Amino acid sequence: DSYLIRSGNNFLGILNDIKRRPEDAANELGVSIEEINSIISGKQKISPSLIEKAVNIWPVNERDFYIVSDDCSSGILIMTSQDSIKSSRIMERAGKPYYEYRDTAMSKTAPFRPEWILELCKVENNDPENPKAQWNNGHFMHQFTYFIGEVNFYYKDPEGKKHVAIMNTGDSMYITPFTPHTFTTRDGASQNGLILALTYGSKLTGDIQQELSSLSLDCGSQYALDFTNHENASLSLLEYYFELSNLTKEKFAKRTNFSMETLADFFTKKKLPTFDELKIIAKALNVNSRDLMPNDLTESKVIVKTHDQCDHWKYPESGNYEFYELASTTALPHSKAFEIDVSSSEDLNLDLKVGLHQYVYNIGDSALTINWNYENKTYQKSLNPGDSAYIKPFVPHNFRGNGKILILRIGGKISGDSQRELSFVGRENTQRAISETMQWF
Amino acid sequence: PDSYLIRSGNNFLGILNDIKRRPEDAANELGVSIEEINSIISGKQKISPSLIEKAVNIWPVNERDFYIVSDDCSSGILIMTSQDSIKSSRIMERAGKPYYEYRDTAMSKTAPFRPEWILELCKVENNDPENPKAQWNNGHFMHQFTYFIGEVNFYYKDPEGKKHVAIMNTGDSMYITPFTPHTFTTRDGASQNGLILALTYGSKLTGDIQQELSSLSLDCGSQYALDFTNHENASLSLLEYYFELSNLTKEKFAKRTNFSMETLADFFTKKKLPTFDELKIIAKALNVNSRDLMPNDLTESKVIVKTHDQCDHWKYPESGNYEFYELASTTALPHSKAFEIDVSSSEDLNLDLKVGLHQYVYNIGDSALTINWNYENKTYQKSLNPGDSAYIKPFVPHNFRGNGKILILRIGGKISGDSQRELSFVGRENTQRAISETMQWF
Ligand SMILES: [Fe+3]
């Protein structure tokens, strides 16, 4: 069984990390040595009673004993429009139906939650202060949203002031976590407005939040550096990595051959270091110049993009699709969002391949085909209007037919730092890096 | 009033909110008492593995999501005594003879350290790397920093499988990349057995990230590993990767950057390396930061060896309480710092040390020391005897007082890097609010 095999390899990896042999685990856990090997080999699943014993005697967490089962074994997971309709549920705010929510395609293995949210409350004006709008206070999640119909998008700025974005079909937005927001339909639309939202944690949720939450408020918040703009962000990084080195300013000065005057102007923001001097500073702090660099610019908390601003182009050179760049922010370089006009007759030429998680939604009125390859097998399935899909990273695929799709790409926890650490380990070691099948000696 | 059950019920209510379920909805869909649902949320009783199995079968949730980590370091600093390490001792035999003595040192469920005290019981009659007495491992997933005490031979294999040995002495140090085969022995004739402090830790490859990667096929998962063989190859791999995410054509890429197709072809064939000005242009066209396209300034060796005579040192702070010795490190892990600290300070009441990293401390000297620190608006003071170890949470202000010597390892954990930068854009006020919403009693 794929679950039992991966569950034993996971338990074996826990034992390797605490430097316990199967015999050491058996004695400390008070169980037979064959019982341990039975778990490691995947003959039987570990019992919660044994997990409780391990957590009571070892610096391990119960979380580490429960693996995620792959509910997307073919490479792509499609949910039908019919299934989504049956999942409909009405959300009432202020004692009246406000949202209609439907499940769309998602995987237990993918770190995103999509939202199909129909706007049932109708507003008579575009006033952000309209009492009919029922606000939330924000969430500790990233959120991309695609607008279909006459949707008003309300949000509050950091100072608490209410704003509104008058949206139409093809508009898109991103909101920084904890941005309060809500959605309504403008009175007079031929039908209720609709949003397709992608909610995801990126680098903020799961055990990353649990590492942060086990710190005091005073300590945990000190990770948040002053990134209000480029100049302040570059000083914040200079201060953080200076503290990490535990150098004095004199030693820092002698090591960079910078004068104390040149050093003081940097730490007082009087003079910003050049890129050549940032190379010298990074070498002296034993970090990379990349680590001292801020983002090229600081983005707005709220990014709104109307469809007229979406640059577009044909892809590939042969012209099978027309891509449309939806809303994006450089705070999330691995979050991509596209409108794709598909015009290509059915062929098994796989011309799309991207190293990201993908959420697909057929927003057109015509049926499309999706072809892909996964584990040396080529598949072909239909993606009707209202159908959605999850596509695993690096899956080679195409879309065929005449129609329109929504494509949302996120990096999950892999893209960025983890990917770079996995690159220094070497592709040769990827299999063992993914799931340990060997005892360490 | 159990803190764990309160936070666990807080976590359970968060799951229901993410799947758009009221507590009433959960009792119906799970077919269980609403008193039982509320009892779990309010922290009166722990949830059951049977109830979790039902939720995982009907909802887009994982069993992993229901179990939170309990803080075993509520004081901010956790100290393990030399006697606790002795009690955790276990002898490991290889080739039918005792080879290592393992002892645990300070580690927390909050911390990614797996620090081991390891005595080299096997004595070798030569310094031949191919000596059959050395019992090799297969490499492991943990990153490893190592501090050497005594006449230790450090064996390791190069990328092509050839065996090497480094002749280490007290104060030498090393870093070894995950999955590099290695082993340790004592040189015969030494007055005592060699000892290593083997500080192994995960970084950005364990936990939720490993589960996300492990649900992918090998051919898919392997494509995350970019060509970082050298600075030039890494620059092209990043350029290629982020160009693929943008889903632009070469022509549209050329028009967006105002680069010619020939200039663009020179970049993608490694014939020309983009300058920093050109990199900012490329990044803007790809909707990323130039920092995202930059590789590390150089690619480090897989094995880093540093003898003590190569360690730079300096007085810290200006007043002069400490002498910091800069041990082995690699820019592949810019948040991993290792120090040998000579403490010679008696009457100084200020907490003069503060760093935003997880810390491991080991008293490697012959004299006891005092640790002073503040955490949760409380001031503490404890003694760190020879052989005692400590874990210090990030940003805990502290000092060391007395005359002695300690080993210090600082690692970034899951937060430093990408997570810290995302938190910085969220803001310090909302970072506090996120943590505050985990402590809420419902
Ligand atoms: Fe090791």
Image (tube, coloured by chain):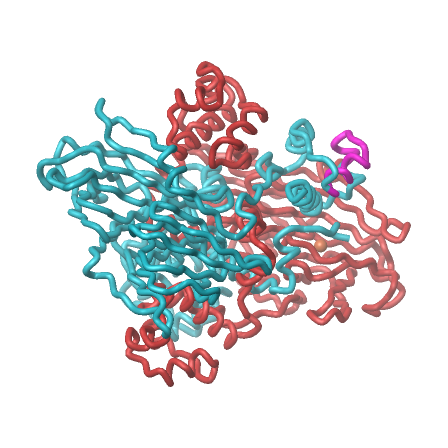
Chain colours: A cyan, B red
Please give the name of the residue rendered at 29% of the width and 33% of the height, measured from the top-left corner.
A100
Most extreme residue toward the front is: A345
Task: Please name whichever residue, A399 or B274, is drawn nearer the observer in this view of the structure.
Answer: A399
Task: Please name whichever residue, B196 or A178, is drawn nearer the observer in this view of the structure.
Answer: A178
> What segment is highlighted magenta in the picture?
A26-41
Labels in figure, total? 0
For residue B383, what is the image quadrant? Answer: top right
Q: Position of residue A316 (x, y in %)?
A: 38, 71
Task: Please name whichever residue, A419 or B168, is drawn nearer the observer in this view of the structure.
Answer: A419
When the figure is inspected, residue B255 is found, relative to residue B47, above or below; the finding is below
When the figure is inspected, residue B138 is found, relative to residue A97, above or below; the finding is below
When the figure is inspected, residue A427 is found, relative to residue A438, above or below; the finding is below
Apparent side of residue A321 relative to residue B165 in the rendered image (left or right): left
Q: Position of residue B242 (x, y in %)?
A: 42, 66
Q: Is any part of residue B397 visible from this angle?
A: no
Q: Position of residue A90 (x, y in %)?
A: 30, 29
Apparent side of residue A346 relative to residue B121 in the rendered image (left or right): left
Q: Is any part of residue A391 visible from this angle?
A: yes
In the rendered view of the protein, which quadrant contains the N terminus of chain A?
A: top right
Q: Does the magenta stretch mainly form a helix, a strand or a loop?
A: helix
Task: Please name whichever residue, A294 or A135, is drawn nearer the observer in this view of the structure.
Answer: A135
Residue B198 within the magenta-colored segment of the rendering: no
Apparent side of residue B288 relative to residue B303 in the rendered image (left or right): left
Residue A37 within the magenta-colored segment of the rendering: yes
Please give the name of the residue rendered at 38% of the width and 38% of the height, measured from the top-left corner.
A82
